[PDB]
Amino acid sequence: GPLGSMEDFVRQCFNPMIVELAEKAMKEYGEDPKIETNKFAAICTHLEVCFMYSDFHFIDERGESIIVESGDPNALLKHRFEIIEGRDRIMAWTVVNSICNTTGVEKPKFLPDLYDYKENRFIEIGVTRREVHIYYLEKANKIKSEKTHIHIFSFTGEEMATKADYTLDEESRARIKTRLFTIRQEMASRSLWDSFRQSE
Ligand SMILES: O=c1[nH]c(-c2ccc(-c3nnn[nH]3)cc2)ncc1O
Ligand SMILES: [Mn+2]
Ligand SMILES: [Mn+2]
C-alpha cells in the first residue's frame, strides 16, 4: 500500500495530551519531532503505556488497592500511582524528592516512570521492539539500584518484570498489550512498522 507519514500516524492515533507531552520532552532534549519521527512515536507509545499502567488504580479508605474504571471514583480514594514520566525535569525531580523524603524510599539516580504507593517502590516502564530479556538487561544495567522495579512490554505480548513480580492483574496488562498490538498493526497498514521496529 501507500507509505503514510509517521507524523500523521502520531497525531491521528495518540491523544493530544500525550502528543503534546512528547513534543515537550523532545524539545527539552533538543530533538525535533519532525525529523526523529520514529523516536517521536516511541516516546508517545511509552508515555501512553505509563498512563495506562496507572489508569483506574486506586487505594481505598481501608488502605487497600482497588480498580475503578467508571470515571467517577469516590472522593476518599487515592491514586495508586504517582506518574513521573511526562513532567519536565524540574517538576519530575520535585515529585521524586517529595516521595523519597516522605516514604523514606531511597533516591533514584535517574528519573523513573512511576511510583507505586501499594508496593512502595519506583517503577521503570520499558516498551521494546526487541526481545524483552535483552531490553530488561539494558534497563537494569542503567538502573543499578535494587529498589526500582522494572516492567518491560513488547509489541508482541511478551513481558518481563523484576523477580517475576508483574505488579498488576492480567486484565490491566492485557489492556496495554492490546493497545501495543493496535499501534503495531496500524503502523503496519501504513507501511511504517518495519522501519520503526528496526530503528530501536
Ligand atoms: O523507558 C523510557 N524510554 C524512553 C524512550 C525514549 C526514546 C526512545 C527512542 N528513540 N528513538 N527511538 N526510540 C525510546 C524510548 N523514554 C523514557 C523512558 O522512561
Ligand atoms: Mn522515563
Ligand atoms: Mn521508561
Image (spheres, helix red, strand yellow):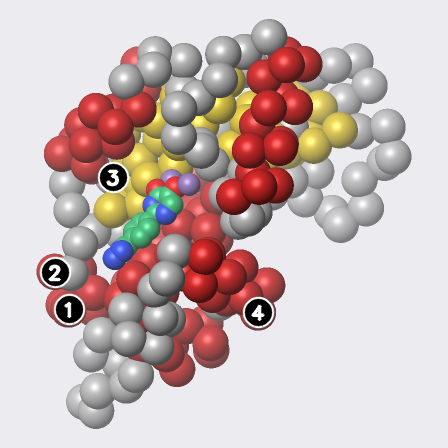
Badge 3 residue CB within 8 Å of ligand 1: no
Give the distance between the C-alpha atoms of the residues marked 4 and 3, in whole angstroms: 28 Å
Give the distance between the C-alpha atoms of the residues marked 2 and 3, in whole angstroms: 18 Å
**Extreme-right residue of the structure:** 75
Give the distance between the C-alpha atoms of the residues marked 2 and 1, in whole angstroms: 5 Å
**Residue that badge 4 annotates:** 16
Q: Amino acid at mark 1?
A: Ser
**Extreme-bottom residue of the structure:** 2
**Residue that badge 3 annotates:** 158
Mark 2 or 3, nearer chain start: 3
Closest to the observer, 21 or 179: 21
The x, y position of residue 34, in whole percent, is 34, 77
- Asked if residue 142 is positioned above or below residue 128 in the image, the reply reads above
Which numbered disc covers residue 195? 1
Q: Amino acid at mark 4?
A: Pro
Callout 1: helix, strand or loop? helix
The x, y position of residue 63, in whole percent, is 74, 14
Callout 3: helix, strand or loop? loop
**Residue that badge 2 annotates:** 198
Q: Is residue 170 visible?
A: no
Q: Amino acid at mark 2?
A: Gln
Mark 4 or 2, nearer chain start: 4
Give the distance between the C-alpha atoms of the residues marked 3 and 1, in whole angstroms: 20 Å
